[PDB]
Amino acid sequence: VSLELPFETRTWRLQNGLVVTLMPRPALHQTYAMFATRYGSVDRAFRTDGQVHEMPDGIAHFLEHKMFEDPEMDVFARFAAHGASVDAYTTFDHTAYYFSGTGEIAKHVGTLLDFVQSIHLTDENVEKEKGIIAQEIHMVNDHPDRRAYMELLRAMYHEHPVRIDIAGTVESVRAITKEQLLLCYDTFYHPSNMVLVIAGGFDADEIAHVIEENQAKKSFKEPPAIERLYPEEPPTPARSRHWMHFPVQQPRLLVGWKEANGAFGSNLIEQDTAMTILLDALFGPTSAFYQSLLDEGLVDKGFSANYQLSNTFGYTLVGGNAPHPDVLAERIQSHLARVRERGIDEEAFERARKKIMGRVLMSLDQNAFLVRNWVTYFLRGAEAFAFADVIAVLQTMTLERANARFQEHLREDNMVVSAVLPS
Amino acid sequence: VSLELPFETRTWRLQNGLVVTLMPRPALHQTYAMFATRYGSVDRAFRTDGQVHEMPDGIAHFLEHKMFEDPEMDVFARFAAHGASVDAYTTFDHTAYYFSGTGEIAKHVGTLLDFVQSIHLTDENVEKEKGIIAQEIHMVNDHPDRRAYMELLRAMYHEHPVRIDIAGTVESVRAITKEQLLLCYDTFYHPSNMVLVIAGGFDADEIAHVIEENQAKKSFKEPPAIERLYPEEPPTPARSRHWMHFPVQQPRLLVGWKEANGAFGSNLIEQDTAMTILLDALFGPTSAFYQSLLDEGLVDKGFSANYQLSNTFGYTLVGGNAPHPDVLAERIQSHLARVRERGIDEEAFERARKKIMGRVLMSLDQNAFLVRNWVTYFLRGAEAFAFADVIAVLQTMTLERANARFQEHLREDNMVVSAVLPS
Ligand code: NA
Ligand code: NA
Ligand code: NI
Ligand code: NI
């Protein structure tokens, strides 16, 4: 049967181009709300209003930091004084602002729209924030987990911006100007480039009227047209093998595979869902392969396999702590060589599909998951997204399709093997 | 108004003494179930059936490991093949077994009762598991976070078993015998010493009948009488200051305060709730003290203040990463010296009460929280526990009571300051 959620999903588009999705769930105390923009760390270059721009790295994340500045509000206290709290993040391809709370939802939604739809930059506070971000960048270059990850990306990618960390570099952050920040904010923070998604214990009629009234009272420009400009990234890694020494107390191994290109909308949903099942079957905590590695002390319970897919890039990562990183790397390559020769085992595949169907069903209980995922798939091109779309891929996915995905993507020539070794 | 939950809470006691609480929430896909025993790492000594016993440390946790052994089941696969997964933990004063899943809840509850109500020990598999636990103990002595924590406890406590880690030592684990394990299992795993709590998308009439039928078909002994035997722990620390060097990349500071004794039931609920509010007001992420420490680079966002209270002990812990551990320790003591002289600031206190009321209200949305907390407070003596009890303490708590709690407990003579310094 097609997925029937127990609650209403109300999705419409405002006069100013903003898409809104409300999921009222009256039995819950929490409301969780997210306002996000289709703009992230990888949007280095773009054309808008007839001109080509190439920015220093770091702008999406700089704007995130500065979004909370307001001469007429402590933004965090405005939420907190009325029973909610607010946070944000920047990722590769979107920036998100979100709160959760238990009452006065009308006020909080108003505050969320208001603080994201105005920016307050001065030459002074742009200078101040550069120092704060440079420091954050230095600290994060000393974090071993983040370092191993960034070494893999740097090895994998020749030119794609994903090879630079989300905050940028010290050099690039230092070159950012107020003018650039304002250009990017005006270009990407238009409501036509954004999405507002809310789930939990709120009155949908009440909140829908508050949003319309808030937006109707503001004045927006014509929507900017954006041509996204990205390089022709080679399908092979820049370096296929890397190791380095770092003050870590045990070795760490990361093996990755590079997608030749990104994906959009329903294609992205299908490929992402298919990898979730495949990686669980190959590497998951209930796989005989994982149990054999654990029994042999080659991994610990923090071992994981993850997939990341966006419009202009994608990759698989597998690994974790590895007392014998060479041995673990060999076992992974052997495992894959056998599946490559012999085909995916059907029984492991059906157990995986059933685990992931359950995991998704249970996750649809959570306001945060419902919201985050509606936002994420919408902005990545599923303009009419529905969770039934995910469930339906989980139901209809086949062993042939699992084999084709494996053959396409988990290969030797698009693979990077990288290690961090104790100093 | 007294708290009204949106769902039914059905609490009764079976013929064999087991207390069951079901919280059906029909709108949810997940059911989360926990079967726990009032027995943990600190129950080193006890009297039962007319005899005094003193055990080697480690038994609660040894039984946890061995509970999953079954000649007629892969216990994990029994849950997994029908859309659930199972795990367990041992803590100071209870051991818990739990699953979450999306269907065939009747089967899973049956499997949960069945695998916890029989144990399958052999001289052989007791030997095997000793090696596995000794290794786990060695690994955990090399984990810096766990090490700093255990150094604090070892400094704080003279004789109380809480000073030994949950798994015991290599020596004590090695002295454990099958006979002892069986004695502790027979004594503490009787249904009269346990609790079963289930929340989520299940039929309460269906599951209540399955539980009664499962228990009615088994044969239980007369409930063992247990006299809990614990030492007269001094109210002052064994050592009030400690530092050590460890392969860590930044220093870590932990400051703790020792309760003179533990608490029971409604007294424990009140004191635990009161500390949650107080610690947030003193040290929380929205406190001016915390913001001043962060602005000065004396802490990072992993800084935290936590409270632990049980029937026979309790303590407060505050700290985290500390680039200047001496300076941070001084600032904490100064902060507390001013509040000690001047009284708790009322405005910070009301903001804290409102944050924690919200946090609790939002947490009551979660099957896992509802279940874990019902279990925990019940086993610690709130024999008629209700979440309204917690909410009511949050509503009625006063500034005078916050000052009295502070004066009683956050003092200089029951305080331990400890640091781990980079090698
Ligand atoms: Na703003
Ligand atoms: Na068992
Ligand atoms: Ni940042
Ligand atoms: Ni263990």
Image (cartoon, coloured by chain):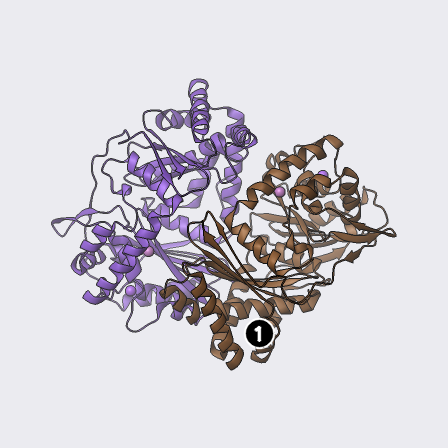
Chain colours: A brown, B purple
Q: How many marks?
A: 1
Image quarter for ligand 4: bottom left
- Residue A233, given in percent of the width and then of the height, sits at 70, 63
Q: Residue at x 29, y 41 (%)?
A: B311
How busy is the neighbourhood of tag 1: few (under 14 within 10 Å), some, or many (20 plus)?
many
- Residue B277, given in percent of the width and then of the height, sits at 46, 34
The reply to whether residue A351 is visible in this rendering is: no
Quarter of the figure with the C terminus of chain B: top left
In the picture provided, is A21 more to the left or to the right than B117? right
**Residue B189: quarter of image:** bottom left
The reply to whether residue A182 is visible in this rendering is: yes
**Residue B35: quarter of image:** bottom left
**Residue A415: quarter of image:** bottom right
Q: Residue furthest left?
A: B50
- Above or below, A131 against A55 in this view is above
Q: Residue furthest right?
A: A50
The answer to which of B251 and B159 lies nearer the viewer is B251
The answer to which of B392 and B153 lies nearer the viewer is B153
Identify the subunit bearing mark 1. Answer: A
- Above or below, A77 against A301 in this view is above
- Residue A201, given in percent of the width and then of the height, sits at 60, 49
In the picture provided, is B420 more to the left or to the right than A177? left
- Residue A64, given in percent of the width and then of the height, sits at 67, 43
The answer to which of A209 and B6 lies nearer the viewer is A209
In the picture provided, is A214 more to the left or to the right than B221? right
Disc 1 marks a residue whose amino acid type is Phe
Say which residue label 1 marks. A406
In the picture provided, is B186 more to the left or to the right than A113? left
